[PDB]
Image: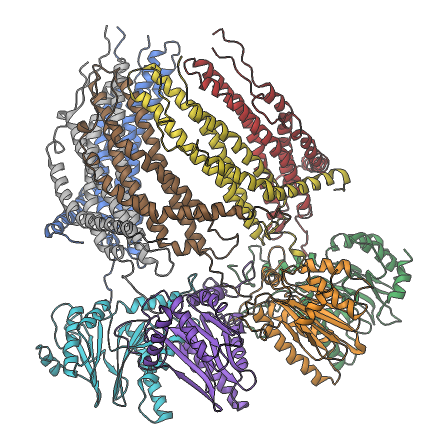
Chain colours: A cyan, B orange, C purple, E yellow, F green, G blue, H brown, I red
Amino acid sequence: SFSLTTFSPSGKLVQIEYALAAVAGGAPSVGIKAANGVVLATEKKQKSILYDERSVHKVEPITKHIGLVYSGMGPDYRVLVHRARKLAQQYYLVYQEPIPTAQLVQRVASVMQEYTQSGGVRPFGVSLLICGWNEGRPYLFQSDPSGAYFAWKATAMGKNYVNGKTFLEKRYNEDLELEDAIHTAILTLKESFEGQMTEDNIEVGICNEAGFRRLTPTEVKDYLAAIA
Amino acid sequence: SYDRAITVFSPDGHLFQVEYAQEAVKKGSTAVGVRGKDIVVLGVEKKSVAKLQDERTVRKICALDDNVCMAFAGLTADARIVINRARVECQSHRLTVEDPVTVEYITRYIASLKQRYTQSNGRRPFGISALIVGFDFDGTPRLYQTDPSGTYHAWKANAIGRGAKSVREFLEKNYTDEAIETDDLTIKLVIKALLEVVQSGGKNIELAVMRRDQPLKILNPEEIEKYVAEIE
Amino acid sequence: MSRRYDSRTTIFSPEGRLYQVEYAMEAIGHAGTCLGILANDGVLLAAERRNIHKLLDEVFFSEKIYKLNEDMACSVAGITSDANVLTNELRLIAQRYLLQYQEPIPCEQLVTALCDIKQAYTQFGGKRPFGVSLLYIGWDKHYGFQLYQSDPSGNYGGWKATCIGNNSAAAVSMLKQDYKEGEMTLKSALALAIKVLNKTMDVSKLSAEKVEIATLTRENGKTVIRVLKQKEVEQLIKKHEEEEAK
Amino acid sequence: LRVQPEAQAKVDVFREDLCTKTENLLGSYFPKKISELDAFLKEPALNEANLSNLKAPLDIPVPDPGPVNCNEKIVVLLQRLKPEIKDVIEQLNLVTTWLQLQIPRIEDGNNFGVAVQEKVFELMTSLHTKLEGFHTQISKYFSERGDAVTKAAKQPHVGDYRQLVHELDEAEYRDIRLMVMEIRNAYAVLYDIILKNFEKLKKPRGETKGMIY
Amino acid sequence: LRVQPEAQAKVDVFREDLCTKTENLLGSYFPKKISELDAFLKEPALNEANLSNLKAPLDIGPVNCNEKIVVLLQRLKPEIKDVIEQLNLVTTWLQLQIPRIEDGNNFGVAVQEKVFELMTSLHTKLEGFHTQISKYFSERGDAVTKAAKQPHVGDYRQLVHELDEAEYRDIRLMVMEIRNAYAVLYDIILKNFEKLKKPRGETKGMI
Amino acid sequence: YDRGVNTFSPEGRLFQVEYAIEAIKLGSTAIGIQTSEGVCLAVEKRITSPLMEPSSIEKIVEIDAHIGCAMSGLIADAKTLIDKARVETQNHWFTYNETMTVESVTQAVSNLALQFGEEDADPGAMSRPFGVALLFGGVDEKGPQLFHMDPSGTFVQCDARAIGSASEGAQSSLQEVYHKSMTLKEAIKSSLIILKQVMEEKLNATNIELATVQPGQNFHMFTKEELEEVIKDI
Amino acid sequence: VRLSGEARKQVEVFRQNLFQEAEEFLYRFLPQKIIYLNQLLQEDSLNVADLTSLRAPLDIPKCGFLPGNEKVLSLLALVKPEVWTLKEKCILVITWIQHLIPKIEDGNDFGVAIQEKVLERVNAVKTKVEAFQTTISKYFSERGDAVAKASKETHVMDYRALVHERDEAAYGELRAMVLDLRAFYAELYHIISSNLEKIVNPKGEEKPS
Amino acid sequence: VRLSGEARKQVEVFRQNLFQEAEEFLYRFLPQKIIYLNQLLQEDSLNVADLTSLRAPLDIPLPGNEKVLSLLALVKPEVWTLKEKCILVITWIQHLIPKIEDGNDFGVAIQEKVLERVNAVKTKVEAFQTTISKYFSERGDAVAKASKETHVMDYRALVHERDEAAYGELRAMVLDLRAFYAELYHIISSNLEKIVNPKGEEKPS
Amino acid sequence: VRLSGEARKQVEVFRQNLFQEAEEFLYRFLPQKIIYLNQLLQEDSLNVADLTSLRAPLDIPPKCGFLPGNEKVLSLLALVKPEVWTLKEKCILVITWIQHLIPKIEDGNDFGVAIQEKVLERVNAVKTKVEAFQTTISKYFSERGDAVAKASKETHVMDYRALVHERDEAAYGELRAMVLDLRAFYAELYHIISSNLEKIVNPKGEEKP
């Protein structure tokens, strides 16, 4: 019942320091907010053909208009899934409306802070990247295990995330349609990913006026033709 | 919850915890008080003002009741807890007894908290030592100091903070039946006690006085310079 | 509960100090520069922005500046994690005040209420202390315009002008010189804060994005809190750049 | 400290040279000496089947009731080994300072990226210590042999003086093959180990990092 | 044991004498010796920028050493004898201020033990400086002996030239060492003097 | 350190209990005496400076009308037991409507001595052992009785007992002065003789406190008047 | 940095050869050299229990020729080559184990720790083998100065017995070296072969990256 | 304290003048001499490793070595000058030592490790000069002793080991001395913030 | 074991006799020797400012004239030597006197043990400095023994033969330093013991109910 996270002689938290170093080496994940939609393209890589791609999906929706991707530990993420989804449920219980992305990320990031204080528990090993659609304005947020959530037009997360950020710094700018947002998210994803690129290796999903939806492997193959 | 024994014995029986708590008391600012005839005078020295910090929030002279005031030297954070909890219990005693609170009553209501919280499970010993001074029935003054170990004593004149022993040396020698005989002598002797620990400051010194049934009164800095004006 | 895993944060130093508390203020010492000034016609609170990137959004409000209630506001220097809980707790405390007393909370009551919570965690519980130092501004019916400063140890005090974070001692040294007590108003204090911000900040090319300024004043019986728009800050930059060089 | 525009720039040029020497050290010097020390041990001097050919005759007679010289073969084999030791030591000092330039200031946070640099730094000094020992023994092999020879001529009495200087020839020769093998093994092993930890060696942390620590 | 007013007061006065001395040392004797030997290094004899002037060539009995260097070594000797004696007064006083043994309250122990080891190890280095003074006397003397044994190789005369260099180079550095033995340690003692004069003792008497 | 308060020694004894008895040597000296005419208690105020008031120092407390008490060791732990011993004494008269035997007084207090622990306890549990030694004198149906307890909680009937820093040489001195039928007033004389030898200061009328209980008189503290008449008999 | 394609080829050819070098010494030399020195120590040359006849006494007066000990010098033909051979091959075992050190990690290093603890024991063998190289050459330098001083002194005869004590130490070491070198072959085989699985597999390479 | 209240400004000699004097050597002397040896080590006098070409002619079956004085002339003042600056860096940090206290040892531990590297450099440059003095004593003693060997060509041929080591070490001295300038300049500049300001003095009442 | 009743009582008498015998020294002689050397350091022989006359110039050209020691230093040693030897005797008597106070071996009651060990360690540390003076006094004879010999051995160098005279002044300067340190040891050992007599004499409390 004693806190496992304490202040270092330099003032920095030692436990959360390794949490941020853990999510830095996770699966490469990128996202872009352009025009009326946000593109989420992650990496699902299977170590053999026996693996069923339809059983486990890395891109999961939080609700109709909100979706979330991740780079980091598997088990700690599904704990975030249940609690964040139950937070959206307890939201809809009280407020009977779709949850805004700013309020959703705020109280979920507060759960990450509870385990930097309460004893006998380790902090989360997952850095969440949240996508949301409210009042016609798209939302792209980035949260790490430290509990501090930011906002980005485009960013990168996972292995070699520094390159993905610099690449989008050069290539990406304003006035990009959702079709260009997908194509640009694929190009920055071609850099971090290594090897042959198929529809099963990448899991892509978007959020627009119609809400957050995941892309089927059929239309993903159409984008693998370097068309849009 | 967090349940463990904090303060534990040593090979010599001394308590390293409590001893380090008294070291933080020694590093506090110098505060002093002296029992007069019908009056008592408290004072403390605060030199830290470049005109920036406000003088309303700095006050270390606190009143537990109309007839009981106090001053503290130590960690300013631990004092705010003790002063508040002492006032809650002091007025809860006026709930149990229509008569006011004798200074010795509340001093047991205070030093006992430093007894419990020192030996309690998971708790921490207090790093403060305060002078509880007030007037008992018939107008007899009383001056009591607490200890982070939980002990308390009675004193005719006492001081706390850095150089507290040096102030007592001037109290021990210069306090006689001639001392604190009238009002003019009580005011001068408390000031003269602080004049040695003066670090070239003529205003920063703060003083307060309580006479009989009158409430605690703070003596303004302008009259401080007038009473310090007569030295030789 | 294996003993070997407990650091026993309640241990006093041989000089009577707390290690976890002293390490907390050091982490605050690396936080960005945040200052505030108490003036006759209003209170002024300004701060810099350490995070600067071309891809940042910041489409909401200020960074380290929060609003406690209608009549009060605060700034932040420290770990942004512990700042979110304190900002929540301060708002909870100030609201729990509205429950019983149903009046705007005095600026003195809200400070001592959180500090009692800070002390309690350093006293017991085994949990680490908080790494955030907070400044407070606002108006009350008794004392009027107020500016306060808080430390993670639970200690606090009133201030006419102060600074926290990086370049704190440098700004305090300038406040001991230029600041005129009971003379300069909110308008004159605005030009003074910009002068102190520019000189104490070694990073050149101060822009409306790189800095943030918020004002709180009482007009016609209503507390008016605002954050100056980037164009309004750019206008102040045009004013200060004539009074710097020219 | 005041800014010197020319002096600080020349220090950067110094760091540029260490970056050039480090790249030439891993990519060029190491594999060239691996293959060179391959043919050096395959050389019939060190591949010699009968070591009596490299035995320099020294005959100190004893009375019953001279032909002293240096050994050209063993000395030249050590004459080639000494600069190979001297060159790699100078190169280890170049990457030692280059590592020091890549080590940030003293900080406890994320100091394990520096600890990885400290492990390789110990590996650089461990090889340096052995290389210092190699050349030190070689200098001692020359001093002790030349002394054992002149002490044999000083005391033409005990026959072990004649046998001692003969065994010193056989000892130094086998010392050549061992030192060259150890040094040659040190090129490829240290090379492969550096490339593993080169991530932390060159970049202990990134370039410019951190988010609200 | 019984109390003897004669022998006991002799110990108390002796401890109070070293207390008055240590105060007279820090207030007067130390800063006087600091500025004295700081000007001793500022002497142009130790400021010589050309070591060829101090090279004494051998006549190759007509054998000598550089008289200027020997005098600098003869001036270096009593100045080191001056620092050793004045520090023994502080060294003894600190050993006479030792409070009764306690397992805790070791801050004052660390204050006394640190400066004690600094002064003790300094006295060892100061005695090592005396060894260097007598060494350079024997180094050039034995180098001339080898030069007189084989007056052929020119490096024999260059050896004693390197010695004259090594002597004067180390003299200026040893003068810098004994200058730090005064001032650097004086600043260290002055910082641990004011409230740390008696870091343990005259403390427990809070009440 | 690297152990709990419940950790046994290699000899099988609690460290916290051992150090508790060792801390009594830093307390105040009090010498009780049991006689056929009553029980005598004496203690020194230990005034280190004239500024203190001797009225605030009470080292002899009254549990019941016929039952007295003495104090030493740690002061903080004693004030908790003195109040708890009083409550249980009145809980006796509240239940059985009679005066508690001093042996049962030592019995109820000895129960809370070793209760200390960490796990499986309540919030009202004590962390550290008592650093206080107590002397219970009094008169009951069996006559004057004088008892003693230590931090371990063992209570033993004693004819004479001394506590505090000077208890080492005082207990050995009690065996010399106590012979057979020696009365209360004679025990008071021998009490001041041993107490004056063991103290470092001078014996004065206001320097020490003296209280006795009798079979025909309730426990009584001698005031400054009577104390001057007692010290005069030396 | 930058590297040529042949630079990695020099490492791969080195890795393959270094692998076979440790494979030969483990599965050929270690088993066979134990019975070697076991029969050598039990051979009549090293099995002589009389050390009085193995001494090399010399007359102490055209003075007579003063040889060394024919036994000690000839019995080195059994010792000396095994001293150089074992040291040369222990280097290749040290080089092989050090070459299998993966990327240095601040955790999960237990497989590397097993390698390090084997490196210390194999180097401890190499250290004692180097001490044998010293004893071989020291006997010729020590006895040479000892017999000459025994030759310079006709007044004191017992230096020959002091010279005899160097003979007992020499032949005592001759049996001790073939005993220790055999123990080395035995200790190396038991330590390497049993811990071989952990040295060849210091890391599981299950990293989720 | 009962100390004399005079000579209060006499601390400004070392705490200011010598303090700023040591500064001038940190940001000027140290970086200026890094590039000096960088070009000096690259000099072809050091780069030639040939045993016979570097050394003086040795006539033995009594000449010395005059060719070593070409390098020693440049090496000796460069090795000694840093040895003095190391002392000035020590004292410069000694004035930055906070008053004796238990805590706040982070900046103290940094200063201890920096002073350890300064003492490590001062010790190594002291061993350089000692070896420099050994060149004259040994070269003279060797030729005097090597003159005894006539029929022995083995010893005389191996005396050239110190003839080669004389020059091979000087190149190692110049290289290491340059690494000392780079080490002292880089470590002090990187930790300059904590070395100058070990204690921020943020403690309120 | 087998405990002889007669032999066990003899040791108890001796542990008591040396216990009271060392008390005579710790009480009487220790403070007496403090002011005894206080008059020794104030001797006008140690107060001489000019050391040029205190050296003993040697006549160095064998028929060379007789070269004794320094009559100034040797005369000062005549007073210093019996005080150094005596304190070395006292120190062991203090060490054994502390060993008499070693309590019965048990886990508890170790607070008096930690105090007497630190006192005995300092007495042994001072005694090490006392026998260090024993070494330096014997060193001055080895210093001047090798110096005067090599000074008279070398007639070619006219300096080193006259430069060994600096060790005469160095022996004088260190002698006045030893007189100060030898007197300090009497003061250092007395104050540390006298102030700690509370816990030194009574380390064990003898409480075992």
Q: Is residue H133 left or right of residue E1?
A: left
Tell me what residue is drawn at x 60 percent, y 21 percent. I72
Tell me what residue is drawn at x 62 percent, y 28 percent. I85
Above-or-below relation of E181 to C93: above
x and y, in percent, of residue A207 in the image = 22, 85
x and y, in percent, of residue I48 in the image = 62, 26
Placement of the C terminus of chain H among the 4 image quadrants: bottom right
Q: Is residue H176 left or right of residue C145?
A: left
Above-or-below relation of E157 to I30: above
Q: Is residue I86 left or right of residue A163?
A: right
Q: Is residue F181 in view from this perspective?
A: no
Above-or-below relation of B12 to G186: below
Rendered image quadrant of residue G70: top left
Q: Nearer the viewer, residue H166 or B87?
A: H166
x and y, in percent, of residue I31 in the image = 70, 36
Count of marks overlaid on the render: 0
Rendered image quadrant of residue F100: bottom right
x and y, in percent, of residue G139 in the image = 30, 24
Q: Nearer the viewer, residue E189 or F45?
A: E189
Q: Is residue E77 in view from this perspective?
A: yes
Tell me what residue is drawn at x 56 percent, y 48 percent. H8
Above-or-below relation of E168 to H119: above
Residue farthest toward the bottom in the current orientation of the protein: A96
Q: Nearer the viewer, residue H177 or I117?
A: H177
Rendered image quadrant of residue G62: top left
